[PDB]
Length: 144
Image 1 (cartoon, rainbow, N blue to C red):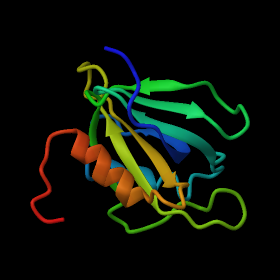
Image 2: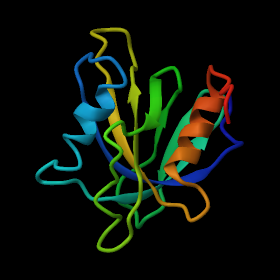
Image 3: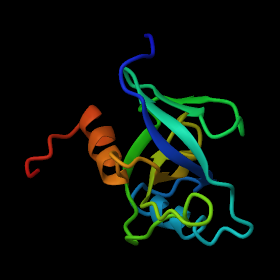
């Protein structure tokens, strides 16, 4: 209904449309089409907020792009990269792990967009962002 609770920092990469792939392959078909995406998109610091199935991404870098709201209804899969790779650094020095999610908004043609993100937090790695984003949605963990 509203939007206020969680609010972390991540690095925005780019949304690479998969065209109805699956989920655990959209991260690879995106990581492989983003880490090498030539030309590569500019890495911007964004603020990842999770409020009642409502992911918010605000530009906290230097006013690069507006803010968007991706409801978890769309974010089907939100895990680290299977290729065990990292983003191409924030911008010259600064290695940051790589993680994306698959957003299936609208049940038209199962047209999903795998968005890439690099952890930009000295106290919030991409694994912790993937352990939280998955803890907020369906799951349990069992082993943690």
